[PDB]
Length: 595
Ligand SMILES: *[C@@H]1O[C@H](CO)[C@@H](O[C@@H]2O[C@H](CO)[C@@H](O[C@@H]3O[C@H](CO[C@H]4O[C@H](CO)[C@@H](O)[C@H](O)[C@@H]4O)[C@@H](O)[C@H](O[C@H]4O[C@H](CO)[C@@H](O)[C@H](O)[C@@H]4O)[C@@H]3O)[C@H](O)[C@H]2NC(C)=O)[C@H](O)[C@H]1NC(C)=O
Ligand SMILES: *[C@@H]1O[C@H](CO)[C@@H](O[C@@H]2O[C@H](CO)[C@@H](O)[C@H](O)[C@H]2NC(C)=O)[C@H](O)[C@H]1NC(C)=O
Ligand SMILES: *[C@@H]1O[C@H](CO)[C@@H](O)[C@H](O)[C@H]1NC(C)=O
Ligand SMILES: O=C(O)[C@@H]1NC[C@H](O)[C@@H](O)[C@@H]1O
Image (cartoon, rainbow, N blue to C red):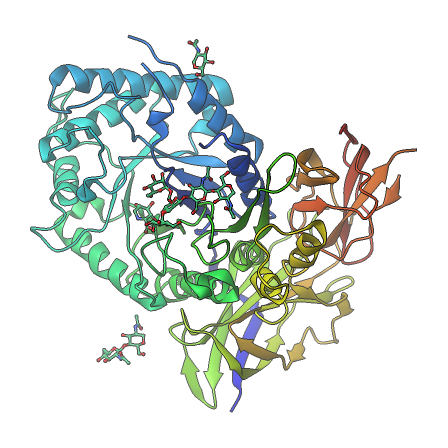
């Protein structure tokens, strides 16, 4: 008996906030070419689909009274160039200087350091930019994640105050949260619980004032292979904080390491394919629907981050918890690195197509209503037209997922009933679909027999499996209703996209860059910020040697790899957007390429 998915496009319920646009990693480096390509891939997720890169040990990128901010400057500039912000964990020993936070002199030093860098980058990027950054405490303080730094309970509070007072000294508009830990039942997690007690009731190291600013409470809760388990753990902790610290009742809670499984490096075959990709969306669905959709209890939940920006290492290029697949091709002159877009990362661009309002949606199987705590679920959105640039949109993301278990031998019949689409000019819909059969670069890698140093052609073939299967813009039936009967696989993802034709064509592509990969092979990357619409089919890429179009299959991801048959890559590249109604936008400024 089929699953029935119902969407009412006229019933725009409440604000839908894109609360999941974050990633992270821990260095074992961050300036290496590998890492440069990685963040080019992250920033390429369309429509600002990933905003924050929560980076450990950022204050080991600074040497030592004055400091060398050269390495930190480089990483942050790198982030900036890919339209990303750091999850700025005030974490590190400033290359070995700081050792004890019960040393009164060291607490003062740390304050002045924090003020120093904060002011530095306000001058570098502007207060309007830096104010968006989530400054954070040392990651997992209860896990003894300290190196040679001594950090007792008392020391952690001194540390915190200095972080707080130092940031304030730069500017009061700068946000600060913590502790970034798990919050297990007392006497467990003393430093995490101790922090809240201090912020709530203790006195400020510097000002002697009762109460210390705490802008958000971040925690780490992981699902141990269960998607709903994450949400369950969050409720328990969040309620314990509502009742124990009544001042923090409205304080936003982040979960900046909300992963299905602890241990990023541990190889898992589900991490390789759409199994991960579907489960990540299930978590986001579970969160939106079963927590943030006016379910009278509404805890202030603002951020979910998947700590999955790590780079893979051999012999596990796909199986690790990473957005991209790394290949260290060691047998060319010289050795060069190549990255592949895993299903999860492709899906972060599917999620990205959702808009500011949630629509009413219901999933049932033969009468019985099923919430997102089931193998199938849906997130539906609608958009209120801003300028002449955009028009009305509906984003319907349906998922099929049994968590960390895949089922290749089963097919899931679904009937989508869409109703109540506000009438308007040239309404069309576009399906986008991902499964392990049709969209697994890991799948292709294995068809090609697991080459360790893939060739150009092997790399072309593996790449062809990144983008989801799409169908040409078909006009919507009259009445503002659509009925489809897709046969979904387990796992899969299906995004039906309904768009009305806006007044003016799309905006101009900007910030175009060419990035060398190897002989006769490069990365083209850009930005959609000035495009101002989500109703896009593909990006036209033209090449000049003296312009003719690079004939490629459709893709809206803001990153393309040019690996042509001729080996000819030197010349000039321009890029423009193409919408669902065949309309061209303005070409970006041409970018030259010398090899
Ligand atoms: C092409 O050439 C590149 C270098 O140019 C090679 O890349 C190296 O690949 C190996 C992968 O085997 C890497 O070594 C591995 O590092 C892992 C973690 O690195 C850091 O993190 C841990 C803890 O977080 C630290 O302890 C460590 O000091 C590092 O800072 C380790 O987990 C791996 O050890 C595990 O596997 C080995 C088997 O390989 C077991 O013996 C161990 O017991 C353990 O389970 C491993 O040491 C290495 O970092 C890479 N170097 C670089 C510069 O990238 C490629 O190997 C090469 N390609 C081919 C095909 O050979
Ligand atoms: C999500 O669904 C599962 C059912 O699969 C719920 O788990 C059950 O919870 C009840 C509590 O009333 C237990 O007695 C059962 O033993 C659980 N069932 C199984 C199969 O383990 C879970 O609580 C649901 N969670 C949410 C947040 O709705
Ligand atoms: C800081 O360190 C970098 C990299 O090690 C070095 O090149 C640079 O000269 C240093 N800058 C200053 C001002 O000392
Ligand atoms: O779960 C992990 O693998 C790691 N745990 C410890 C670190 O906090 C985090 O960066 C990683 O996600």
